[PDB]
Amino acid sequence: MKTIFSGIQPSGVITIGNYIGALRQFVELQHEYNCYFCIVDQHAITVWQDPHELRQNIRRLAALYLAVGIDPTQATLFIQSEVPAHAQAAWMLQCIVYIGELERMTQFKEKSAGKEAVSAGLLTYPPLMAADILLYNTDIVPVGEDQKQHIELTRDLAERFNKRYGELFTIPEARIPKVGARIMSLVDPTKKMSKSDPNPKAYITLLDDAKTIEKKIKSAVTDSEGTIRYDKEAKPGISNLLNIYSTLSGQSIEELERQYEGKGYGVFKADLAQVVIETLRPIQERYHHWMESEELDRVLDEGAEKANRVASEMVRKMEQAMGLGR
Amino acid sequence: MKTIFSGIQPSGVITIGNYIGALRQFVELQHEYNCYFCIVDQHAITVWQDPHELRQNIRRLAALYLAVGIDPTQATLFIQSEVPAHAQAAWMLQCIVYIGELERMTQFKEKSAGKEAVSAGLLTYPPLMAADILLYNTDIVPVGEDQKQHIELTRDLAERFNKRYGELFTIPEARIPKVGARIMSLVDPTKKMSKSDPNPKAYITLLDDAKTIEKKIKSAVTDSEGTIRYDKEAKPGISNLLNIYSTLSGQSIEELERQYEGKGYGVFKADLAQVVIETLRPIQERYHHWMESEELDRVLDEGAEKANRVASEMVRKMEQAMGLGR
Ligand SMILES: N[C@@H](Cc1c[nH]c2ccccc12)C(=O)O
Ligand SMILES: N[C@@H](Cc1c[nH]c2ccccc12)C(=O)O
């Protein structure tokens, strides 16, 4: 089948927005395509991290990905650092990428007006990300609007390498998410929902307990009209809430409007709070079952193992072309 | 015992000056100290390389080191790329080093007034070099006046890592060769002898054949005072020769001076030429023996093994501290 590579920054918290926009759809994709889900812990180290928190967030993320419904026998789930080829191929590519290319990256602006105290990791992480991708001959890389820049560079490195040393890598394509909706902040309906929002009331986490989901939805910003009708502009807040309600319950927007006809936001919010709790419940159940189970490790184990099989043969061929070793 | 780490760039052409200044001393030292001789092929790739050449020079140099007298049961001799812990540890170190430190690196001058098209690996090989040294707890690194700068950085990185994560690394020390024998070039006695000299007659290669040694020596530059007397200033050429002669035949400089009291440069050169030929003879043989012998790879294999055995361990500990993997 076609291959798909997806790197996951270990951070132990993914929003209902991530779930709805991309994650959820993967459970389907994993039968049509050959998926790889790498918990890129080496990339997470480019910025300060607490060792214990990071070690923890790596298990959390794997627990949660399985909990959501990723099948470890169908797809491949693994931790980046337990597959050495990543770092090995990262070095080889660093050697074919020019400094300029990495400097002119619309993300290295992190150098902040004379910071200087920036890890070289920040500057060099793109060639590692190219490795993550290229090592498995991936075809599609499900990234957002923002990442596109990195995809292009890996595409460039792939070809540069191919022409200099021979046809080895597959040029990857940056495919966008399905969504067709987008989940906005509950506190500012114009802004997009994210884990990195300074206000916790802005998002709902797949591990938020009922009491907290109840609390956050009540607070979600609506408007003064008092009617449950879809209106992108004019009624941003309601329209968002309706969007969340609809994708999770399977009921149309037209349907939900008709249902909440002469009802106000008070009950609407109380209803939504429920549909969310009813939807996260099994996930939070399964998740804890995975955090307790030693079967988790056995999964990561065969994950790496399956990944290593391919990565290695790729590096072998890379070292072969470059002229390294024997 | 104490550990000594030495990275060797693959070039297959080491001069009689390198030999006299460092190599020779190791055939002895390898019995007291724990020595690692790493053929840094990953570093050699930061600049344009031809696959065949690099692949070749790696053998040639392994052969050479054994020929000169490195006892593989006593010391460890391995190729860099064959021990993954090097790249792995290189990445983690790139993450605790700031971009400034790498730019203010007095060697990055190869940036050519803004040539811009330089391999990022060029800007980043210092962290790899720190890896190489640090992975083996090495106490001493025999580098010349030229590399000092890099040893300073690795001393720094090592110190930084230890403070953040705890005592793990030995802060190495750069210990130079035994002073007195600084072998200048055969054509310019104020210039140092190097494989990188554009005039072939400025140096003698451990594999230079008799006819070539004879011709280069004869053309060695001398003064007109026509006496075989040591004179650092005034008589540079003769003092160089007297140094090459002395260090090889074991005679004292004065001994040679007296022994030549009423002789000219014609005979002195004819004598020197043969004592050089006599010294390389067994090396050139042992070198060809090793080259075609399949035992070479076996030696390299047990080198990887021994190296990896320690490297893997140190990486495991580094990953532990940084918070990577499981
Ligand atoms: N920084 C990217 C990095 C990344 C690493 N490996 C990947 C694989 C696929 C897509 C992105 C990546 C992100 O968080 O998305
Ligand atoms: N550039 C140094 C690099 C080096 C790599 N690995 C090393 C290990 C020890 C000392 C120096 C190094 C040289 O050619 O000498």
Image (cartoon, coloured by chain):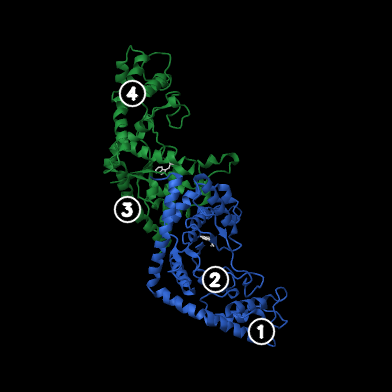
Chain colours: A green, B blue
Q: Secondary structure at mark 2?
A: helix
Residue to which mark 1 is pinned: B265
> Along the line of sight, which residue is nearer the eye, B59 or A285?
A285
Number of residues whose C-alpha sits closer than 10 Å to that of mark 2, classed few (under 14), some (14–19) or many (20 or more): few
The Cα atoms of the two marked residues, 4 and 2, are separated by: 78 Å
Q: CA distance from mark 3 to mark 1?
A: 66 Å
Disc number lying in front (2 or 1): 2
Residue for point 68% across, 87% down: B263
Whether label 3 lies within 8 Å of ligand 1 gets the answer no
Which chain is mark 2 on?
Answer: B
Q: To which chain does the residue with label 3 belong?
A: A
In the image, residue B154 lies at what x, y percent?
54, 54
Q: Please report whichever mark, 2 or 1, sits nearer to the chain's N-terminal start.
A: 2
Q: Report if the CB atoms under discs 2 and 3 are less than 8 Å apart.
A: no
Callout 1: residue from which chain? B
Which amino acid lies under the numbered mark 1 shown in the image of this protein? Tyr
Q: Are marks 2 and 3 on the same chain?
A: no
Amino acid found under the numbered disc labelled 3? Arg
Q: Which mark is residue B25?
A: 2
What amino acid does circle 4 point to? Answer: Tyr
Q: Amino acid at mark 2?
A: Gln
Q: Position of residue B2 (x, y in %)?
A: 51, 62
User: Up-down: is A140 above or below A190?
Assistant: below
> Compared with residue A198, is residue A71 higher up or lower down, i.e. above or below?
below
SS class, disc 3: helix
Instruction: Tell me the SS state at disc 1.
Output: helix
Crowding at mark 3 (Cα within 10 Å: few <14, some 14-19, many 20+) = few
4 and 2 marks on the same chain: no
Residue picked out by circle 3: A309
Instruction: Say which residue label 4 marks.
Output: A245
In the rendered structure, the answer to whether residue A174 lies left or right of residue B24 reads left
Closer to the chain start, of discs 3 and 4, is 4
